[PDB]
Structure formats: C-alpha cells, structure tokens
Length: 169
Ligand SMILES: *CCC(=O)N1CCN(c2nc(=O)n(-c3ccccc3C(C)C)c3cc(-c4c(O)cccc4F)c(Cl)cc23)CC1
Ligand SMILES: Nc1nc2c(ncn2[C@@H]2O[C@H](COP(=O)(O)OP(=O)(O)O)[C@@H](O)[C@H]2O)c(=O)[nH]1
Ligand SMILES: [Ca+2]
Ligand SMILES: [Ca+2]
Image 1: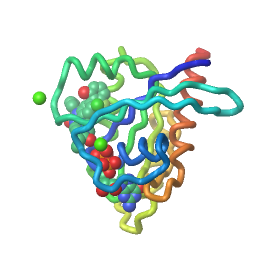
Image 2: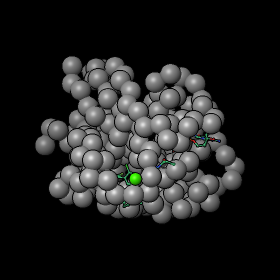
Image 3: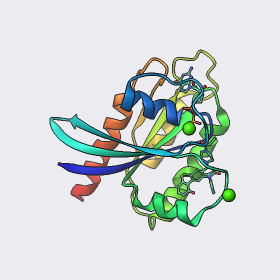
Image 4: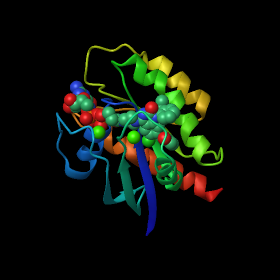
C-alpha cells in the first residue's frame, strides 16, 4: 500500500491535536498539553484504495528551527487549520502556506484549508472568506468540529485525495 506523511499545522489553540486524536482514537480531548508534538500511524481506505498515513501533529514555539524545516520538508501534504472564532488564526493561514512552500522549494504542495470549531455559534471568520482564500490557493476547504467529529474524516481523506492527484503529476 501507499504511505503518506501528513502534517497538521496552524496557530496555537485551533484544534490540531483535537482533530488528530479524534481521527486516531475517536474521542475529543479538551485540555491537550500544547507542548506535545507527536506522530500517529493509521491505515485508511479512501475511494476504495488503502493508504498508510503517518500524521505529524505540530507544536513548539513561535520560532524558526532548521530542524523543524527538515521535518516539514518531508511532509507530503498539509492541513492548514484555523478556528472560525479566531480571526488571527485565519490571518495566519497565509503565513503557514508561505513557510510550507519555502521549505519545499515552492512545489505545488498538497494542502487542505480546515475551518475547525464549526460547532461554535461565536464565528468571526465568514465562510465566504475561507472559501475565497481556498479558491485563490487552488485547494479544498473543509469545515470541521473536533468536538462533534463533523468533517474530521473528510478533512484527512480530502488531503489524501490531493496527495494522490499531485503524485500522478
Ligand atoms: C501552542 C503550540 C502550537 O500549536 N504552535 C503551532 C505552531 N507554531 C508555529 N509558530 C510560528 O510562528 N511559526 C512560524 C515561524 C516562522 C515564520 C512564520 C511562522 C507562522 C506564522 C507561519 C511556525 C512555523 C511552522 C512551520 C515551519 O517552521 C516550517 C514549515 C512549515 C511550518 F508550518 C510550524 Cl510547524 C509552526 C509554527 C507555534 C506553536
Ligand atoms: N468547541 C470546540 N472546541 C475545540 C474544537 N477543537 C478543539 N477545541 C478546543 O480548543 C482547545 C485547543 O485545542 P487543541 O487541539 O489543543 O489545539 P492545538 O493547540 O491546535 O493543538 C481545546 O480546549 C479544545 O478542546 C472544536 O472543534 N470545537
Ligand atoms: Ca496541540
Ligand atoms: Ca527554542
């Protein structure tokens, strides 16, 4: 089977860990230690084809690291996560994409825009803004809630679809 390195990126508190733990362990974690950066394995069937996923849940400090760069370069696809009640995290999306392209020689890197915390009524980022941003980048946009599990499989599955499309090229 094919094996892909996925990387979950985005600002502190957007739900990177909650999304990943939901996918792997099927429960919602409310106070996940923000210093733990770990990877998880999962075998999945998507569009009738099995892939092994190696998923890195990023953390660390707001700092440049040449070693982090090295790890990020090995990623084959990225989830760009923001929270719909956090305008800063949405503004940050552009900068995460800039860093991904930087470390991967400006390749047309497989990416999915993820609007997490879609269960909350406290929205500050309009869906149209997110759709327009994904459109400009030529990437899918998926709305998720790690809390309710809405769209969690979809977000990761869609990223695998993007990697598959890219590796045909
Ligand atoms: C609360 C802990 C947590 O979740 N995080 C999220 C990831 N963190 C983080 N912060 C940050 O400022 N950057 C960054 C560094 C240099 C320039 C621009 C940025 C942001 C605004 C895009 C990163 C950058 C990355 C990163 C790197 O370094 C290379 C390639 C891709 C990439 F996403 C990462 Cl993984 C995490 C950053 C703070 C703690
Ligand atoms: N209401 C709601 N809260 C969430 C969701 N995802 C994460 N959270 C909460 O937001 C906080 C940060 O989540 P976490 O996964 O630790 O964010 P990370 O710093 O990006 O890894 C935690 O208190 C989570 O319980 C969601 O989809 N909906
Ligand atoms: Ca985390
Ligand atoms: Ca440091």
